[PDB]
Image (cartoon, rainbow, N blue to C red):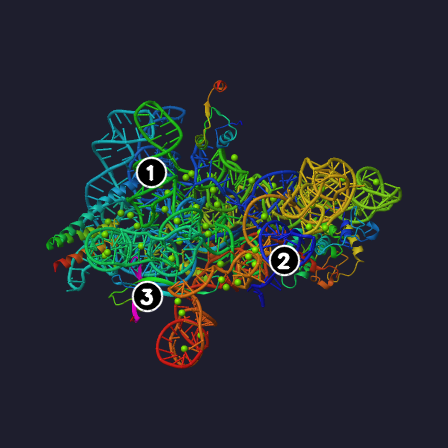
Amino acid sequence: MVTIRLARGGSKKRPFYHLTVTNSRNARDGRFVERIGFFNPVATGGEVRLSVDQERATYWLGQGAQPSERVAQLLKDAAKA
Amino acid sequence: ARYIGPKCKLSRREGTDLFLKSGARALDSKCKAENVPGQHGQRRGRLSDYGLQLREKQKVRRIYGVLERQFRGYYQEASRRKGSTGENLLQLLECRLDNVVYRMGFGSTRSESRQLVSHKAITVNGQTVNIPSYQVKAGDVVAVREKSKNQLRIAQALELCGQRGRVEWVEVDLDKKAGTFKSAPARSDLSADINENLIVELYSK
Amino acid sequence: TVRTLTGRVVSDKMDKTVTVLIERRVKHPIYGKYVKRSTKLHAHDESNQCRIGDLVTIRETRPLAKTKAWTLVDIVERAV
Amino acid sequence: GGGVGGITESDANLALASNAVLFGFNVRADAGARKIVEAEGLDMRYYNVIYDIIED
Amino acid sequence: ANTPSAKKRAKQAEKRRSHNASLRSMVRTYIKNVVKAIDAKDLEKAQAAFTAAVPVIDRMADKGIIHKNKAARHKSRLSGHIKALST
RNA sequence: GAACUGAAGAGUUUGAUCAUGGCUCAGAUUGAACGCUGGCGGCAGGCCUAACACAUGCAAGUCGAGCGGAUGAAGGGAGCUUGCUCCUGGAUUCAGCGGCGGACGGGUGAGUAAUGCCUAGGAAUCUGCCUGGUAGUGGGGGAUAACGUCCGGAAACGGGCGCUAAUACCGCAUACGUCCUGAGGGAGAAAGUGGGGGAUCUUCGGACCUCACGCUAUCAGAUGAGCCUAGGUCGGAUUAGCUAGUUGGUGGGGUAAAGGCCUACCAAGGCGACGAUCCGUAACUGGUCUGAGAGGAUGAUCAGUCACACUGGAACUGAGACACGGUCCAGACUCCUACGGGAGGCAGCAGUGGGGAAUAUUGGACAAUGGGCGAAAGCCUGAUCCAGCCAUGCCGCGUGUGUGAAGAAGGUCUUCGGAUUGUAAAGCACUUUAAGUUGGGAGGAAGGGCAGUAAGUUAAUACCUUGCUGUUUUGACGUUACCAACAGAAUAAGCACCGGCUAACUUCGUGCCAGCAGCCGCGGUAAUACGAAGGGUGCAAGCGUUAAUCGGAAUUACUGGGCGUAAAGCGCGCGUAGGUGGUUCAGCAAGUUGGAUGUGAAAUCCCCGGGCUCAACCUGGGAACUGCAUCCAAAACUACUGAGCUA
Ligand SMILES: [Mg+2]
Ligand SMILES: [Mg+2]
Ligand SMILES: [Mg+2]
Ligand SMILES: [Mg+2]
Ligand SMILES: [Mg+2]
Ligand SMILES: [Mg+2]
Ligand SMILES: [Mg+2]
Ligand SMILES: [Mg+2]
Ligand SMILES: [Mg+2]
Ligand SMILES: [Mg+2]
Ligand SMILES: [Mg+2]
Ligand SMILES: [Mg+2]
Ligand SMILES: [Mg+2]
Ligand SMILES: [Mg+2]
Ligand SMILES: [Mg+2]
Ligand SMILES: [Mg+2]
Ligand SMILES: [Mg+2]
Ligand SMILES: [Mg+2]
Ligand SMILES: [Mg+2]
Ligand SMILES: [Mg+2]
Ligand SMILES: [Mg+2]
Ligand SMILES: [Mg+2]
Ligand SMILES: [Mg+2]
Ligand SMILES: [Mg+2]
Ligand SMILES: [Mg+2]
Ligand SMILES: [Mg+2]
Ligand SMILES: [Mg+2]
Ligand SMILES: [Mg+2]
Ligand SMILES: [Mg+2]
Ligand SMILES: [Mg+2]
Ligand SMILES: [Mg+2]
Ligand SMILES: [Mg+2]
Ligand SMILES: [Mg+2]
Ligand SMILES: [Mg+2]
Ligand SMILES: [Mg+2]
Ligand SMILES: [Mg+2]
Ligand SMILES: [Mg+2]
Ligand SMILES: [Mg+2]
Ligand SMILES: [Mg+2]
Ligand SMILES: [Mg+2]
Ligand SMILES: [Mg+2]
Ligand SMILES: [Mg+2]
Ligand SMILES: [Mg+2]
Ligand SMILES: [Mg+2]
Ligand SMILES: [Mg+2]
Ligand SMILES: [Mg+2]
Ligand SMILES: [Mg+2]
Ligand SMILES: [Mg+2]
Ligand SMILES: [Mg+2]
Ligand SMILES: [Mg+2]
Ligand SMILES: [Mg+2]
Ligand SMILES: [Mg+2]
Ligand SMILES: [Mg+2]
Ligand SMILES: [Mg+2]
Ligand SMILES: [Mg+2]
Ligand SMILES: [Mg+2]
Ligand SMILES: [Mg+2]
Ligand SMILES: [Mg+2]
Ligand SMILES: [Mg+2]
Ligand SMILES: [Mg+2]
Ligand SMILES: [Mg+2]
């Protein structure tokens, strides 16, 4: 199906994540349909920990996209704030 | 790497003061600084335009004690920046942490300020920095660690920096050895003998 | 709406189809001069009403044979 | 040229460059060395007792 | 094969092929009866064969042996041929 | 506010000079190799050659809440007696049937010059799981693996007879949509499990109610693929003709779908100097390296597409393959064997031989992000996250700091006066980064089990779902990043060059030898050019050499060159394609100009910021992508159309 998951970038022991809407049978860092924000496990300082597009996320969830476990938790946390 | 060796043949070869000793006693009464180093010292040997450009670049590099690859990086950054790379290079060289510690009177020379910085005795924004290339920004407060405030080196360095000229762009708080970087010193704040046009000419070839 | 192409008729010896030549003018990539290029298309003439020399207009449809996917909609300059 | 292991292209065309006889004691040549030996007229003998080599 | 899954898939696939071939031949024979009846210019035979053949075509399309588009195409062309034959 | 800003020449033809012209040099880059030398860390990279052949491990499984069967705990007990037997129950585990997955993820670049790729379009299709609607899940039937049984085989294992279930398979019933048919009418589905329960009957075997999962038709959406058109995509003319299903029409067949896709008749068409056909070479693109730009060269790592899977074919199953660890046939090559008879495919991760100038470990964990199955614990995962090796690259840091004139001793040169190595050393006094030892110490972690409470669902304080609360539980890396203490200057500098180009010079040996050399050129008894030694100049954990691309080269000249004598006007006409067009009105709108919309993937380049003690590196937003297509507008010029005039 179509899912929303985390694509890993950054560098060794310094991970950065893009919240990506992908066909499920693609590479983790391969082709995607749309990026709807990012997540920073380290952040600190002026860096934000995570940001999401509410509009795009709701639109894709309304079209039948299944988010992962981390994407579900992070999206509900973002909606909490 | 680092140039470690006789730090006065450089002055004789360049033919200018090119401060490398503490300046306590003199320069003339240590080396007879009127002849090029080596056996063929009495010869004069007028040299060509490429030689003049090379000598100018070497003089600047030996003044600030940086090697060739880092200097090329500095030149590329100065060219990238806006507004007349010629003094951009000097702006960028005059902001290194070892040079700033030297200008504040904490060290007698550049090598001793490098000794201090590398050996974890300097804090920039209340936190330790030991990279003698850290580009200090306007408004930082270079200080000395409390466990390193009783070294004599700082005492002689301060009492001897008391008479070399007023920098007038850093305020040193003498009693507790804390400084402040107001801004980068403009071209008119440095000596008007370096011909940076020769450096830019040399690298643009 | 629908985009069309306009050109001359260069052959009508086939049955229920015509050969149309389309002239285009393209600037040369490197030397800058404008040179003229030609395109040959096979168009569909249902009632065989086009003769050599006619200036006509055609549009794109689904393929009707191999090497034939254009259909004509109007004859605008009848040949002599 | 000595060595341990099967007969290879390197020793085949080392023998080719010295008019040498190619002896293999308890070893075999591979496909490429066989191609080279067939192409020219190199003589290659196999053995399993050293005294046959001495006699030859 | 190297793993049990591949062997089981091969066995199940052979069974599937054996099951499917008979049903495909069934559909083909039922269509060929109508085609032969039409080719012989025999009306009542054509209606009898068409009425016998439509249910099996639809049933086998529904089971997944053939695609429903093929069933619709066969029905349409047979109906057209028979209707043209009647006149 | 920014997204740029940018361009050097020199040596060598002559006795000397100007020009022409070739050669060479100074720069920046490599997936580099070799020689000498070698301390540390961070981030990357690592068979470019034989799509050569492969020993050995691992790389794709999961579901008992779909189904029989056999394994049969703890317990309640019963008997006899210390332990056994028996029964009821029964927890766990799966060889088999069955459902999904295996078409993904991973590798390689042989073939392919156009069924590929890039850009812009469109019409005639299908699409498992996913989302939202619509209508349903009623009732029968015959089987078969497993299993028991009988033989053969060295084994691999094979064969006959009997017996049994299912969400396996096949009819029947019905049809909101659905198929075709003209109205008229006809045709086509399913499957049941798991947790609870009020009242009723029954063996609360169950029916019945409820929830969850599942199944069947169908519409829309999302996603993914199939198909068509236009333009572009290497060199060769010492390759000029190519094509008979070929080009078009009709009837028919076939496909999910248009179509010579196929077939039977009819016609003789189709392509080509705007380069067909043929020959050679080659995956393409974003991009990368150079360049002031225009251009030139090139497709490593990263991302998109394509093709391939020992070689040549073919289909089956499936929503999807002509199938990368599936089937069948043939072939080449290895091997087993008990000689009767079978097996194999590392261009998956390690690894080996071979070829080569040359490219690494039979490592750890599923802790994190993903993928398959499951309901959920959970299982699997050489993807991935990490470790190992190698100065291969980029970046950063060390190998100490201040004072110190008997200007020590030694070396070298000397006009024998001295100069230089040189504040260099020693001496004196300081500091401990990195490395060594010791002790502290984050962040990568979301979740899972249990227990309680509150809401919603019903018919119900049941089950279940969801908020929250309490407790318990998780890290390969890892002796983590980082921080504090101790000791001592202690543990750490080489390589090339010094005649001009081109920064840096003298002595001693040798004597057209030995040798050097990028180009001029050095060496034949005072060699700043060979070989050493003193001194010096460039770089520096690297320094040189070799190979290769662009630059300088305006030396293929579009930007931006030439042809009287340096190379260069056909011996001279005529003329075909083509290029170009005297001068007035009027129209049109292809070129041309302006604007709007859509697109031009992400990363990369650039600008402004933010995080690693800095940098490399990572990352947010913007700019750009100079192009393409469609609309609206303008009419000076070119094109086109109509009518004139005479230079
Ligand atoms: Mg370095
Ligand atoms: Mg047609
Ligand atoms: Mg069906
Ligand atoms: Mg001469
Ligand atoms: Mg290879
Ligand atoms: Mg099992
Ligand atoms: Mg792939
Ligand atoms: Mg290829
Ligand atoms: Mg070819
Ligand atoms: Mg029925
Ligand atoms: Mg049923
Ligand atoms: Mg069924
Ligand atoms: Mg279930
Ligand atoms: Mg094309
Ligand atoms: Mg035919
Ligand atoms: Mg037809
Ligand atoms: Mg198909
Ligand atoms: Mg076709
Ligand atoms: Mg036809
Ligand atoms: Mg050609
Ligand atoms: Mg090739
Ligand atoms: Mg140029
Ligand atoms: Mg290419
Ligand atoms: Mg590769
Ligand atoms: Mg790729
Ligand atoms: Mg094959
Ligand atoms: Mg099928
Ligand atoms: Mg395939
Ligand atoms: Mg497979
Ligand atoms: Mg394999
Ligand atoms: Mg391998
Ligand atoms: Mg192979
Ligand atoms: Mg070798
Ligand atoms: Mg190597
Ligand atoms: Mg995992
Ligand atoms: Mg289990
Ligand atoms: Mg395993
Ligand atoms: Mg493992
Ligand atoms: Mg290193
Ligand atoms: Mg090396
Ligand atoms: Mg002496
Ligand atoms: Mg933690
Ligand atoms: Mg010189
Ligand atoms: Mg001599
Ligand atoms: Mg020389
Ligand atoms: Mg020499
Ligand atoms: Mg070169
Ligand atoms: Mg050029
Ligand atoms: Mg060149
Ligand atoms: Mg020109
Ligand atoms: Mg010329
Ligand atoms: Mg001439
Ligand atoms: Mg002449
Ligand atoms: Mg003439
Ligand atoms: Mg003409
Ligand atoms: Mg004119
Ligand atoms: Mg004309
Ligand atoms: Mg982009
Ligand atoms: Mg910073
Ligand atoms: Mg933009
Ligand atoms: Mg107008």
Question: Which labelled disc corresponds to residue E7?
Answer: 1
Which portion, as a residue range, is magenta? C58-77
Q: Where is residue E47, by image quadrant?
A: bottom left
Q: Does E85 sit above or below residue F70?
A: below
Q: Are marks 3 and 1 in contact (CB under 8 Å)?
A: no
Q: Is residue D55 left or right of residue F210?
A: right
Residue F362 falls left or right of residue F212: right
Location of residue C38 in the rendering, given as x and y in whole percent from the top left corner:
37, 63
Q: Quadrant of residue E76?
A: bottom left
Q: Quadrant of residue F124?
A: bottom left
| Secondary structure state at the residue bearing disc 3 | strand
Q: CA distance from mark 2 to mark 3?
A: 58 Å
Secondary structure under tag 1 reads helix
What residue did someone put label 3 on? Answer: C59
Question: Chain letter of disc 2?
Answer: B
Residue A57 position within the rendered picture, expressed as x and y whole percent measured from the top left? 44, 59
Query: At numbered mark 2, what does the secondary structure look like: helix, strand or loop?
Result: helix
Q: Chain of mark 3?
A: C
